[PDB]
Each structure stands twice: as C-alpha cells, then as structure tokens.
Length: 73
Length: 73
Image (cartoon, rainbow over all chains, first blue to last red; front, top):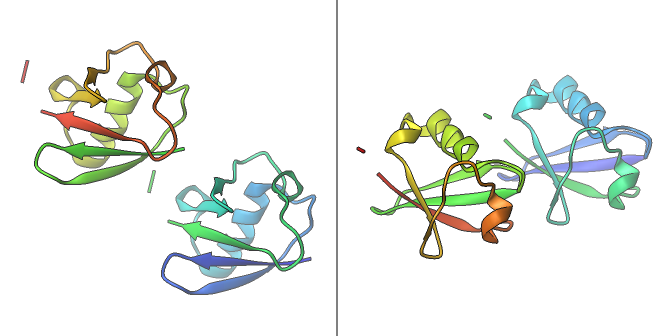
C-alpha cells in the first residue's frame, strides 16, 4: 500500500509498505530515501508514537495514510 | 511519551521517556542534552520534589506533562 510521511517542516515522502511491515522496517525505508538513520527518527500517527517491534496494522494505518516524522537521542 | 522540563529562567527541554523510567534515568537524559550532572538537578512536578528511585508513573506525570528543573548540593 502507499503511505505518506510528513515532516514538521512540510516535506512529504511517499513509501511503499505492507500492514505487515514493522515500524523499524518503516524507518529503514525512510533511511533508504533520505539518509536519516532510524535512531534519529520519531514516527507519529494521530498523536501516538509508533514503537519499534509493532507493525503498521497495530495503529489503524491504512492506504494513503500520512505519518508524521520528527527528528538525536 | 514526551515530557517537558522547564527551568526557573524559562528555557524548556523536550525529553523522550516512558512512565517506567526512573527519576535518575530522567536526570541522565537531561545530562545527555544540556551537560548538567544529575547531582546538580532538582526536579519538581506540581509542587512535589521527584525522588531518585521512583518512576514517572509514581507522580501522575503523563504525556506532554512539564516538570520544573531547579539547579550544588
């Protein structure tokens, strides 16, 4: 499916994922495209922080949903 | 979750923590970002001093709650 990842500043990135993908998988796709290591990535969906080990399907992320990415510890 | 730590003088710091984090854990995160050793940190929430050994969940600190940090003995 296709999801969107929006930064604080405005820039969007399109990703290709499955509900089965884990959150760390997702950060690795964000790593592939923008060079941001996963450890510097905080992902949010509807006010909830997405925790490693979980999948997309754990959070009601659907086709063409938009996460927010917040960028050191 | 995300909590805020406000100094007497105004400056805020954003932290990433869990309810499970101990107070000394919290001071160590404040150490990571601002270089203040934990032994010089006094943390307050709603008029209560936060004591080492306890966790956040011991004090009704929640998402986007704001502690106050007071800075030698």
